[PDB]
Image (cartoon, rainbow, N blue to C red; front, side):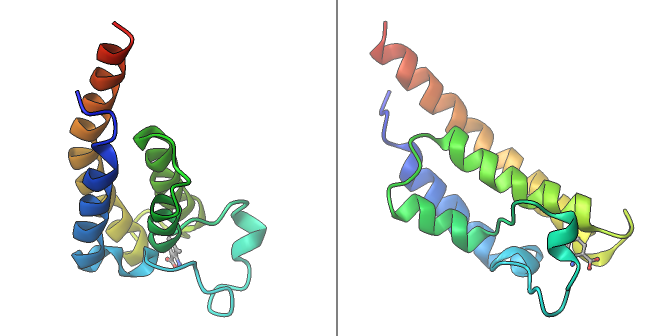
Length: 119
Ligand SMILES: Cc1cccc(C(=O)O)c1N
């Protein structure tokens, strides 16, 4: 029932994501010089270094907020991809499955801790 435990759990999950080869296209903001039409398609860029920095700055109040930004990295990849068979999009799908498999317990534990606090 530790209400703060999600933060280190998210830090550790981001460390695993950064070690995953599938995260490399998503570690830093998409290069606008390499993809000059990116901002014509994508309204809100997001990347894992921005997520980690937001977490480390104490600018997430809950793991749900972190999860919304990570999901935005994946929806941006799906929206920008020219093909559902593209290399970078395929990497995003695998990374998303890995993230969802690991974030589930973080969210469950946090929500349970909050319910216990308000019991
Ligand atoms: C950022 C991004 C997401 C999804 C697909 C691509 C691609 O160039 O195929 C891409 N550059």
